[PDB]
Amino acid sequence: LFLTEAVVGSESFCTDEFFIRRIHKLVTDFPTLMPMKVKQLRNRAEEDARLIQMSMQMGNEPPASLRRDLEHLLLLIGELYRKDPFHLELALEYWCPHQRPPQRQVLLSKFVRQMSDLLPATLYLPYLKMLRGLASGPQCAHYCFSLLKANGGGSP
Amino acid sequence: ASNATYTVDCEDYVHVVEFNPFDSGEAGSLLAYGGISYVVIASCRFQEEDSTVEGIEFKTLKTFHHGERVVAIAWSPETRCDALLPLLRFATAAGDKKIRIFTSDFQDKNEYKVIEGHSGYINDLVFCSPEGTDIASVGDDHTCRIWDLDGKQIAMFILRSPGMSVAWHPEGAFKLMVAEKTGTIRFYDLTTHQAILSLESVQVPLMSADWCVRNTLRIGAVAGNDWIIWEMPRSSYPQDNKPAHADRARMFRWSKCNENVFATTGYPGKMKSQIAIHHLAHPQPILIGTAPVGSGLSWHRRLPLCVVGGYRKLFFWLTEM
Image (cartoon, rainbow over all chains, first blue to last red; front, side, top):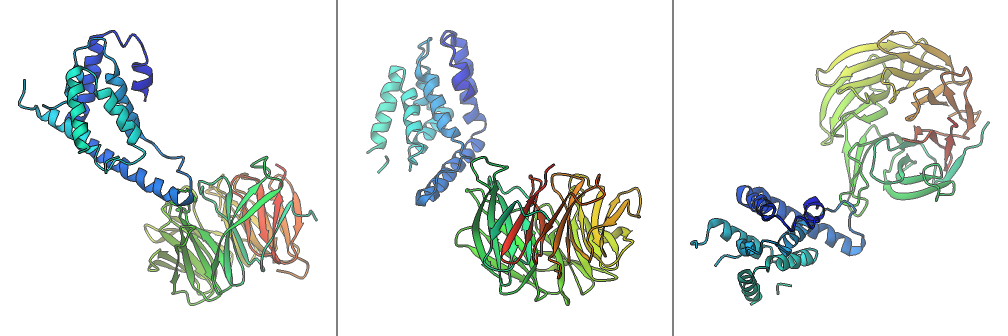
């Protein structure tokens, strides 16, 4: 939340190419160097959400102790690529068709697809916002476009 | 005689009453009271905690059928009213010499377990672990017994007379206090299963003892007609000893908010059971209440407020600090 509001909040962040690259590396290094933890956490969150929400749906109100870091995570991804001053089509990291698909690109693409499979109603918005952020940079445009189009070929 | 500050009507006679001493995560203070054949769990909110409450908001949350006269109630530290995982756990002793552990989710899941092995009446019981896994009990069989939640006896201490009160030490791990009817208070280590120390009362019978939660060096008790205070480790002799009641003191409880304030009750007597609230700086009680016939004495966790059970009523006294 702090990275989303305080860092990128600066319109001067818009300026330095090397700011974007460093943060890009910090964000890409997390799923590459410790995805086990990452997945653990994802699943945990999805599940807890579902459970408490459904429980409340019977007649209660959702517990004030909720924490949607995934949604904040999806918004962060959406905001980070939303606009790049460099316009180097960095978002290309989100797309897997040079390289025989670098393992990193495959895992990330799997991440984007895995998040679309049995999407809880609470994650629906953060996921769209994530996609919105990932479809910048024309090549990326086309690729994510097609990807999602076909994934819908029922997923909300 | 001061009138009670607040009074709540009950279905039947109140034999025991205990506030939850733990944080349940609710805005209201949990209260348990035992009748002739039932245990009621209620939430209390007071005007002194919330300015939207006029006097006392008393809400019954759950009633448990017990089938026997309840003599003592102990809250489990695991007791929480949080909406995500509500858990009510408490233990009771009754006239049938059995302990009952109740567990509830405040919904449909209501379980109880019976623990057997005392050969005499149980006089008092407490949870004796920070984790709420272990129960200590004392009785007329001259034993202090330690139980898991599975009803297995973990330990047993042979007493020299009937055990009259039991209390877990509020800060120090493994220290159980046991008050014996003949005036001896013993401390047991539950790790080593050994008696560490004793205190002796000048008067007998010793009827109730409690730890000062705000000053873990202080112990208060009632023996004969008098209230007695010890300060550890300075002496095995009382620091203070003064009259509590004209005819037999029964219960002693320390205030949870003030280390100089405590309440005592007289024995279920012809002159309607007196509650006396004492302050150590004063030679006389600061408040004298009358309850027509009352058993159980408990202090609110935060407020300078005590409760006594009576004939179909709970009586509350606020003490001006």
